Image (cartoon, coloured by chain):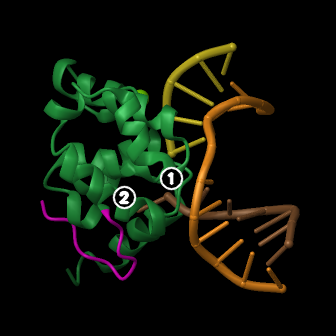
Chain colours: A green, B brown, C orange, D yellow
Amino acid sequence: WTPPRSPFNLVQETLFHDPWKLLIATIFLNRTSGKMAIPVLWKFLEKYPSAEVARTADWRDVSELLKPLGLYDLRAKTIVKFSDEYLTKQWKYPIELHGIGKYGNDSYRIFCVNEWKQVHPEDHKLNKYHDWLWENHEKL
DNA sequence: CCAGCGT
DNA sequence: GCTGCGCGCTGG
DNA sequence: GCAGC
Ligand SMILES: [Mg+2]
């Protein structure tokens, strides 16, 4: 499964090979514009390239890197706990994990596995992508 | 300047 | 069902 | 957007 590139340029389109990075990106986008969140994501991923590193991090150090995005202590704590669970808990879908809800889960189900036809997003940008897929999947 | 917004 | 979390961006 | 409430 290779999810197609869209005229909406969702960041999930480039991250889908690594479900942890795609999910981290969803967290970066919690009430935060892509214009600001996505450039900081690359800085975060340079420093915390995997769940294995992030799960050992001190949330206070993560929070310093996230300050300009707001929600910095909440999100730092989320990222460390999510990362721990991703690696250590049994799960089938990432909504079972702390810090991912329907938006992250829907993103995972469209981008990381081939369940896009079963997903009904509430997030507007994800809905635009999903409508576009229905409209275009034959052509693709 | 500043009240409302952002996958 | 509603709240706390939080910054900088947006643009009239 | 998400968890907590
Ligand atoms: Mg969850």
Taking depth in this image into account, of A137 and A86 the one nearest to the observer is A86
**Can residue A52 be spotted in the picture?**
yes
Q: Is residue A2 magenta?
A: yes
Magenta span dominant secondary structure: loop
Q: Where residue A130 sits: x, y (%)?
A: 39, 65
Q: Quadrant of residue C1?
A: top right
Q: Is residue A17 magenta?
A: no
Residue A22 placement, left or right of A67? left
Taking depth in this image into account, of B4 and A116 the one nearest to the observer is B4
Tell me the quadrant of the picture where the C terminus of chain A can be found.
Answer: bottom left
Q: Is residue A78 above or below residue A48?
A: above
Q: Do the CB atoms of the residues marked 2 and 1 lie less than 8 Å apart?
A: yes
Q: Which residues are magenta?
A: A1-11
Q: Is residue A6 above or below residue D5?
A: below
Q: Where residue A40 sits: x, y (%)?
A: 36, 58
**Which residue has dot 2 on it?**
A40
**Residue at the image position 50 percent from the left and 40 percent from the top:** A72
**Residue at the image position 23 percent from the left and 33 percent from the top:** A54
Total marks placed: 2
**Which residue has dot 1 on it?**
A69
Q: Where residue A32 sits: x, y (%)?
A: 53, 56
Q: Earlier in the sequence, mark 2 or mark 1?
A: 2
**Residue at the image position 16 percent from the left and 45 percent from the top:** A49
**Residue at the image position 47 percent from the left and 64 percent from the top:** A36
